[PDB]
Length: 151
Length: 151
Length: 52
Image (cartoon, rainbow over all chains, first blue to last red; front, side):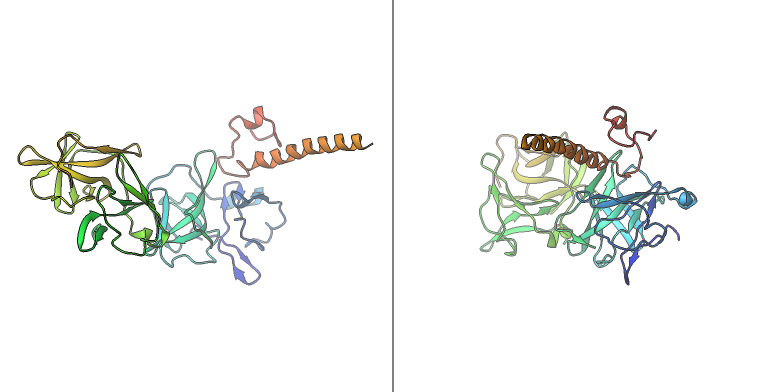
């Protein structure tokens, strides 16, 4: 646990599902079992257009929390499978670093703050762009390269 | 391939045709067909009084596309026949480094991000200035002094 | 009696737009962090008006 949190359901690892402050996300295409099975007894909220189901973190994960940001730099960011070249409003990974089953992985910055959450990819050959949802100072926006797929 | 993306027909090179980000360009001031016929099937939009041509890209090669920055600091930039002296809001070169038929050389700075696409030349002697298309605040413009010898 | 039913349907559509507006009230700020209604729960007063 550098910053490592999970999601897995019925014998297939559904990627990750993390905690941002008071929020536990779930990407709306992920269905099933939480990595922390005390969290499945809480009501989620569906945003199919924004592709999420959100839930309110109780008090007993206050010491388990993690930090995020609202600002956006330009450049390169670390994540668990490697690097992301974010340029021009586009997140790009080396081809094959993602896969279907990498769903709900966060992206943390060069400081550790959660900057976005993955939803899927879109291959451009030598790299592969990334369809995500971020926040942009008081709103979320679904930032999506077209032709996306469920990862 | 530095940034070599070209337009060719029947044996003659009619300059370049690049995919910059969202865009495939074709210089509609010069006739011909595509270089590589995998994109020959795609649509094209012609301009009438500004004489460019557009195509919406398929994603499967978009990693090879270049990046833009639509602002202009002074100095010296890179292009297919070397450096180019950009000063005074104006692009300059010695006489002969561009010939008529060099329509579309993509200009980029000392880290290689695209700022201008060249159309024609002009001179009263030795200092050829390059009539181009330009951008400002991510809007297109077409800049050409009078008496420009057309490529 | 069916005029009574039609007006009951009309206020059913009134609570229908109310509940669709409530879900669309939370679609900006489900738990989208920053955790703030800048003026929306103070003026609009949509639902759960006890957040700062």
